[PDB]
Length: 232
Length: 236
Length: 78
DNA sequence: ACAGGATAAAGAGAGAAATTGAGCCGAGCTTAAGACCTCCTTTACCTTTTCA
Image 1 (cartoon, chains in turn orange, red, green, yellow):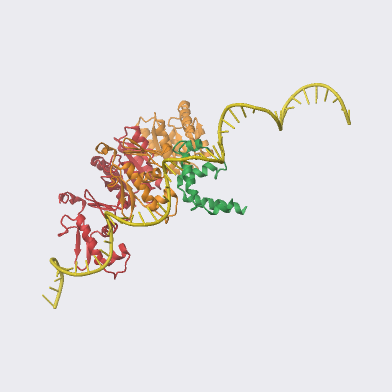
Image 2 (spheres, each protein chain N blue to C red; image 1 turned 45 degrees about the horizontal axis):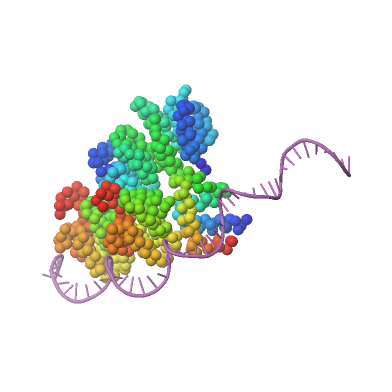
């Protein structure tokens, strides 16, 4: 299902901005203009996340958060507090409110969405590194400043190695990930395609620098850090 | 028990400030000055929280975080990223690293402590590094002080077996059983050969080995200096 | 009804062999969970990367299943 | 029963889209032999210990 988010904020313009941005991100958004309605809706809906304003009328946001934490039905719901951040006292009371995170207003939409994603990953690919950029749509690699066309299997092999950059990948793992074959199938095919990658990517395929062979362990893709590109 | 916090940061001043403030808060703090040592400590200790600077040498903070997420033993450990926060691209790459939170330097100590509390409220076995050695299993390599040494598989497993028993004498029969799985009665002479290769790779003088000692009649012992003495041995 | 529960299990097994992302893609592209086949664009928005990326994953998964290994029982279901 | 009238809901007419499969090719892929470089084992001969 789509994660349910309850946004509780008395600023209709902020509330609308947040709601629009969350819906564009695929969430089920519920909106509340006050802490009393917000608490009742939280109890009724059991949303997957609460974003909670601070300056609601009649009832402060801290009391709302504390009440959500006191109801067994809401005690576990994560609370992302929106705060105007200006006084050490609101800080000290949020330190007792049971907030899960804080976000300073004005916020970037991307930061908000990052926090939402992290909270949801809590309730529940490398396409570029240094000198190598993968272009899936064209099965191509940017290798330093040259474009290199790859075959489908050559590309998938290089991607599999890039996913485990700096680690040795066993031939059986390559077989499983790229070909889906049984671990005991013939690994000799891999030995061929690694060689093509070296022919395309290394300056000297006989002394491969980046696509290393670790005898008895497999192959390792070792790439220089971006700080070293100027030397290579 | 006291919660274990692993702080990984190459800035000794930030690392010290953080460690002092966490200890004042009652945590057991462990410190690592580089991403490789940090990763090895995370795997060895399974800390209750990782604080991970961004710009570590030899291994970027993103690669460290991704590798922690790839290890079943560390995949669940919360990661609070310390970042110099200045470009949306580092933002975009962190958006894929699997970081749990970010904290911009300079930070207020109270904010740091709040994040630590929230991560800890949310959360609720091999020695890979000691003194001058990091073992790098994934590459069959050893960091020895600051030099990379390529090892063969049996040499690596032998060195690891000795590291597991650092400061103790390891019997040849135990090495045969653990590394080779052989019977205690098989020829131990093969081990004697491979031990010298480790000395050839690791000792300054293979004829007068300082670290890979022979305990006559008992076996081999890896004696490593404590981290406090490293400055006296690197020049060797 | 008993050749229905049995089937899904067999399919799920061969699905396990595929990479996590791949199998998720397949389940969503055929509606194995919701009965509703989803487009590219719904997974383009719901999943991390956008459209024209899920198509590649679908082909790279099917090519894994199309091999005589990891999927041969279902051949008789036809 | 039979005739007239009003109407809406369900068929035929066409092209344009979208697929589609078909031949005809060479690019990707596999197979097998041979060579060829690490890693390991085990030997022959030692040096180097702890001890009577």
